[PDB]
Image (cartoon, coloured by chain):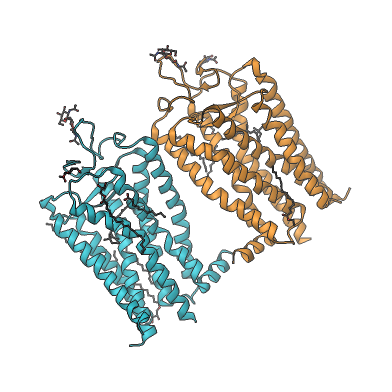
Chain colours: A cyan, B orange
């Protein structure tokens, strides 16, 4: 191995010179200059300060205006809630971690960071599955109502927890990645005690490949066959934005899983891991730009 | 002396232990932990990312709408421009300096950071002077038009440069303060080669006390003597108050240091007032949006 494995960590840095310390015990300045940890903290502070108001204002405007009860309005409402969970539950630990250069909260902080970021990303993915069926049902007419949308909302939480929760209780585990200031799923070690390999295959199949198969099946029909046009256009951008956000992470995660112990450094996963955290803020932005009714209501309420 | 004087710095940290190093040569981790410097950089990064959009949008909306040509509109447009000089000309140096924990750009970086924040703050103060006279004439009619507003705009730049420029060319100097990641006027040392003592008196009298006397004179004449005019007077009251909240803590601590040179204070003493004052680049367009209905509608129109 070209890294350093400990009981609950894998540092992508060789301990041949003896300088590697646990990311739960001391600042990781042996693998990066302090000013680089400070950039990660400036970034996270931005995401929190931007992420909280824009998701709260999406939530506030939707509840205030009773005309926002289409299935799209419910789904965007649900995304704002999970985004708030990501900001307050996970990103506050990311900020404090990146400020101090290591996981000052110990493994409990690593679990919070990884869990809330995994949960929110999966709620967004399975939300895209719901919108793909609604668009397929309404446009093709093979009626999608409030009951269906509200059932879809509960479905996204169940699927997301089926992915985010097991690493909390012994199936795989959350481990620090990159510069050791964020946590994800353990793609790095075998660690048979927690049956790591079977979780990763289950995560990539059930909660990455299968949802994308559903989404692209439905769009395949719409391709191969005015207010609804506005909805369909927004859902196309949301699918594209999701892929830009998560594919770099997904690709590096899968490379590491199939090249365990190989020669990669700490920046390799740091950048796709922190870019993926923009997932907590981009969805309401698309909402404001591409939904005229929601934009008018936000302008009305805020002014 | 309870601090360490260098050729071009004064570190508020004793060198009896030998660890003090120049803020132009090495990170200043001997007087604060690295996570404390990271907070300054995170704070500076927020200000840059908020400061550029709201000032640029304030500029853009004002130019695009012919009906925003009152003296208030001209003064606010001029504040947006100066705020943008603060963000791009000075705050970018602050961000780099906080990230690395010392002035990697050396003395030139200290001059940019101090000059643009001093220039921006003083344009704001002399702008309040201009608005106080305009309100004074408007309410009492003892007329203030578009030529006067543009003349006032030019006046605020000349006065601000008469405060910020001399320290670039040998009357006083810009010097790091606090945790050594921002710069201000040298209240710390006598340094007779730059006649430090006379500049601070000139700054506090001409560029602090005289302007406040003018502002509060015109308010006092007004306090003892339609809808649109009342809206303008209300916003000017808030602008004066917001200036005092932003700058009085800094001016108070600066004047205390001037009169207690070499006394026992640490790096946090000036750091917090110095960085709080940097919010001056942001708050003025926010009052404008909240309290001017014509401007707010023109931005909603422009933005949507
Ligand atoms: C990296 O190597 C160093 C040096 O071998 C390890 O530090 C030693 O750890 C043992 C066990 O705790 C101590 O008894 C020694 O005294 C340590 N030596 C020194 C010089 O500190 C270190 O634990 C290794 N790091 C990791 C993460 O495994
Ligand atoms: C603070 O004190 C230290 C310790 O005396 C100074 O370091 C010395 O500086 C001289 C002048 O450059 C060198 O010749 C010595 O070799 C240094 N000694 C050590 C142990 O480093 C340091 O210059 C002082 N700092 C300030 C800002 O005055
Ligand atoms: C901790 C894990 C939790 C996982 C599970 C999360 C489930 C979230 C759903 C809540 C139901 C909310 C019901 C709100 C009902 C609103 C109904 C409405 O607005 O319309 C009514 C309409 O008349 C109909 O025909
Ligand atoms: C639809 C819009 C899509 C927009 C987004 C497109 C993303 C393209 C890149 C994906 C990441 C692929 C990761 C592959 C990593 C291979 C790295 C490798 O081989 O590097 C070895 C080296 O040793 C390491 O240090
Ligand atoms: C702890 C678990 C938290 C689960 C939160 C679920 C949110 C559903 C949001 C949409 C609910 C339907 C809209 C109801 C409404 O606001 O009317
Ligand atoms: C819905 C939430 C489901 C969460 C299920 C976790 C199973 C994990 C089992 C781990 C057994 C370790 C022994
Ligand atoms: C060095 C640089 C210092 C710049 C100082 C200028 C302030 C803007 C004053 C502009 C007043 C007139 C604006 C007219 C306008 O925007 O459009 C006119 C049609
Ligand atoms: C909302 C928050 C408002 C608090 C604003 C507080 C502003 C405090 C300015 C800094 C200050 O007063 O510090 C003096 C002290 O000597 C050195 O920290
Ligand atoms: C509302 C704004 C309030 C003022 C914001 C100032 C800038 C941020 C301060 C950093 C603390 C650095 C030193 C922390 C020392 C703790 C002991
Ligand atoms: C900074 C916090 C991070 C990087 C959290 C990571 C969370 C995951 C391991 C998420 C996995 C995925 C999604 C939520 C959507 C795309 C598919 C996955 C399985 C890669
Ligand atoms: C971080 C940048 C700083 C601290 C800039 C400092 C600027 C000054 C020296 C400002 C001076 C003043 C004003 C602009 C208004 C209030 C009165 C003064 C003279 C203290
Ligand atoms: C470590 O890196 C070298 C060079 O890239 C590689 O040949 C070796 O297989 C790596 N070790 C493991 C366990 O993959
Ligand atoms: C340094 O601090 C001590 C204690 O407050 C004080 O007695 C002394 O006068 C200070 N030195 C100077 C030069 O003010
Ligand atoms: C717009 C900028 C897009 C950022 C992409 C982030 C992931 C890049 C992957 C780099 C790496 O392999 O370390």
* Percent coordinates x, y for residue B1 in the rendering: 52, 14
Q: Is residue B68 above or below residue A134?
A: above
Q: Residue A281 is drawn in which quadrant?
A: bottom left
Query: Relative to residue B41, is residue A31 drawn left or right?
Result: left
B220 is higher (above) or lower (below) than B68? above
Would you identify the image quadrant in which residue B129 lies?
top right
Please report the residue visible at 70 percent of the width from the left and 31 percent of the height from the top. Answer: B163
| Quadrant of the image containing the C terminus of chain A | bottom right
The residue shown at (61%, 37%) is: B117
Give the image location of residue A171, x and y in percent: 16, 57
Relative height, residue B142 to residue B113 (above, below): below
User: Seen from this angle, which residue lies furthest left?
Assistant: A192
Indicate the position of residue B20 as horizontal and vertical percent values: 44, 20
Percent position (x, y) of residue A67? Answer: 49, 77
State which quarter of the image contains the N terminus of chain A.
top left
A228 left or right of B289 in image = left
Number of numbered discs on residues: 0
- Please give the name of the residue rendered at 51% of the width and 23% of the height, measured from the top-left corner: B265
Q: Is residue B72 visible?
A: yes
Residue most extreme to the right = B142
Would you say residue A181 is visible in this rendering? no
- The image shows residue A28, relative to residue A126, as above or below, that is above
Residue at the limit of the structure toward the bottom, as seen here: A142
């Amino acid at each position: 191995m070209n890294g350093t494995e400990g009981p609950n960590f894998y540092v992508p840095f060789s301990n041949k010179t003896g300088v590697v310390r646990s990311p739960f015990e001391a600042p990781q300045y042996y693998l990066a200059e302090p000013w680089q940890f400070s950039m990660l903290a400036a970034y996270m502070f931005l995401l929190i300060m931007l992420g909280f108001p824009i998701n709260f204002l999406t939530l506030y405007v939707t509840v205030q205006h009773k005309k926002l009860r289409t299935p799209l309005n419910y789904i965007l409402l649900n995304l704002a809630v999970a985004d708030l969970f990501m900001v307050f539950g996970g990103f506050t630990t990311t900020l404090y971690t990146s400020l101090h250069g290591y996981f000052v909260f110990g493994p409990t902080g690593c679990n919070l960071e990884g869990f809330f970021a995994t949960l929110g990303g999966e709620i967004a993915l399975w939300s895209l599955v719901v919108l793909a069926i609604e668009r397929y049902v309404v446009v093709c007419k093979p009626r999608f109502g409030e009951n269906h949308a509200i059932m879809g909302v509960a479905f996204t939480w169940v699927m997301a927890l089926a992915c985010a929760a097991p690493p909390l209780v012994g199936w795989s585990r959350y481990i620090p990645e990159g510069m050791q200031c964020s946590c994800g799923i353990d793609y790095y070690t075998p660690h048979e005690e927690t049956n790591n390999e079977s979780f990763v295959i289950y995560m990539f199949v059930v909660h990455f490949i299968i949802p994308l198969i559903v989404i692209f099946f439905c769009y395949g029909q719409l391709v191969f066959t005015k207010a609804e046009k506005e909805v369909t256009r927004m859902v196309i951008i949301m699918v594209i934005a999701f892929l830009i956000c998560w594919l770099p992470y997904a690709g590096v995660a899968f490379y590491i899983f199939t090249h365990q112990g190989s020669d990669f450094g700490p920046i390799f996963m740091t950048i796709p891991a922190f870019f993926a955290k923009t997932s907590a803020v981009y969805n309401p932005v698309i909402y404001i730009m591409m939904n005229k009714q929601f934009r008018n209501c936000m302008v009305t309420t805020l002014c």
